[PDB]
Picture 1 (cartoon, each protein chain N blue to C red):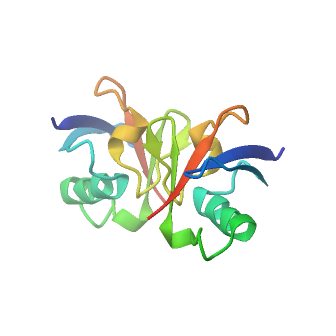
Picture 2 (picture 1 turned 120 degrees about the horizontal axis):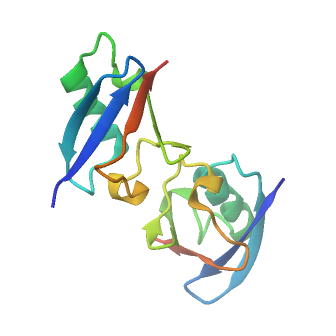
Length: 77
Length: 77
């Protein structure tokens, strides 16, 4: 069943993205870009931080075991 | 400091690869191909299985927290 990810930006703004467990980190970034815009959140610039790691694009989201009740921090470089 | 990975093939053969913790799964596969040959272990065909996951190429090996005292299974498709 779909998983909910709660994201936090450097400006302390929060928002949620729903995805399937087999969809990758790359798909999460694409969803973020749709929600937050290409101007400030282009896919290629996004760095996602969770559990002391920088999340890798081709990993299925399930493999990071992300709890809906924590935050994934989204930074842009 | 370098990490040692112990691998097992489908033919029940074992072997070790030494790498740095920041080197990726892709680098592990390249090392496997050097040790085991392009004929049977081409990088593009290798699937690495550990902790109920298929290891993703661009992830630093450290992020999977692989114990030298367990096996990473290498299959080729």
